[PDB]
Amino acid sequence: GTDIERKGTLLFTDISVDRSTGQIALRGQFDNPEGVLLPGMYVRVRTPQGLNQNAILVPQRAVQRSADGQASVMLLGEGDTVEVRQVTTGAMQGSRWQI
Amino acid sequence: GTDIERKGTLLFTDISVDRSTGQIALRGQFDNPEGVLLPGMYVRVRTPQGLNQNAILVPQRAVQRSADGQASVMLLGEGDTVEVRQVTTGAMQGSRWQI
Amino acid sequence: ANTTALADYAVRNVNNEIRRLPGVGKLQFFDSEAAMRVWIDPQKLVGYG
Amino acid sequence: DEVLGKVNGNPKFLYAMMEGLAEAPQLRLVIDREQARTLGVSFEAISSALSTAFGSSVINDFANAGRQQRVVVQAEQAERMTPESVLRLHVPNDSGSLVP
């Protein structure tokens, strides 16, 4: 609900899994010089899930989705023909899907 | 949800039945050198229910059931005569009845 | 060939027009229209209590 | 059987058959109501679990491209193909624990 962003470093990753929900806890450290971040506030932490050196990004508008959920892109085949080729959709960045 | 498979040995079989669930608890030991198996994680254990040295498996489409629920099979007797032999079905593996 | 998607298209675009036509009394559909299928795994539910 | 033997054995008819399905095997579930109640299991829980797992339960409606269509909940294909899958189901008790 606000435009307040803070950079931080990952301190700890838990080894035990929460029995009631099945998710692991992680703790990061964030500098709070202005006192803006108050204890108990609900926050959403964007954490990097790894770097792939050979990824392909295609704008979201260029990917159609059929009724089965199998997404497709249209390619310029030989002779400038439109080909509907099925692709597997990965991550979402801005307005460009990861293929 | 993963393909991670680990071999282990059954250590302990409880003699007391849980009153709330009517189930017995068992404890096995599994090697975890990489630390992949985390505490609290819900896992499925395939445990052998014994070895049947003379297990006879017949196609399910070969077993008939009468009005009393008794199972029978048609056998090719002497002189290419069809005989009716009553059988008892065990467990089901795929499309085949254990007799 | 996804008979499900084709059947959904037929229901949305074809069956209603035909049923509106004069003279048609009943349209018996030899398939089923789309729906939201939830295939639950009971063992996962057991594991999560 | 008497009629169809006198008739199917009678050459007056090309064929004579049960317009209808012949009797089929059924898997009766004997439920110890006393044992289930002692473990804190209501009959409602068993009925709801069995119905939703095998008979498929229509919960409510959802808007698919402007049309109201059912949402149907059913057990996964691999988890309902054998009679042992019936016995592998669990239901909750009064204390919140799951009983197979």
Image (cartoon, coloured by chain):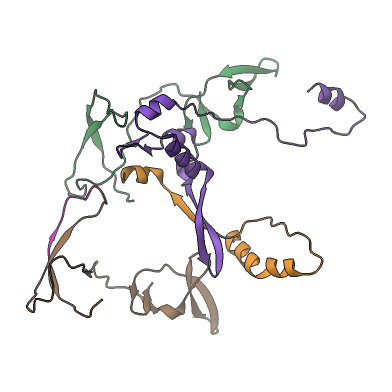
Chain colours: A brown, B green, C orange, D purple
Q: Is residue A87 magenta?
A: no
The image quarter in which residue D13 lies: top right
**Rendered residue at 35%/27% (across/down):** D38
- Residues shaded magenta: A11-19
Outermost residue toward the right in this view: D12
Residue C10 at what x, y percent from top left?
A: 65, 66
Question: Looking at this rendering, what residue extends furthest in the top direction?
Answer: B78
Left or right side of D55 for B44: left
Q: Quadrant of residue A12?
A: bottom left
Q: Main secondary structure of the magenta part?
A: loop
Q: Judge left or right: residue B86 versus residue A33.
A: right
Residue drawn at the location 93% of the way across and 29% of the way down: D12
Determine whether, in the image, residue D67 is placed left or right of residue A18. right
Q: Quadrant of the C terminus of chain D?
A: top left
Q: Is residue A15 magenta?
A: yes
Q: Residue D81, position in %: x, y?
A: 50, 39
At 16% from the left and 52% from the top, the residue drawn is A15
> Which residue is more in the foreground, B4 or A78?
B4
**C32 w.r.t. B66: above or below:** below
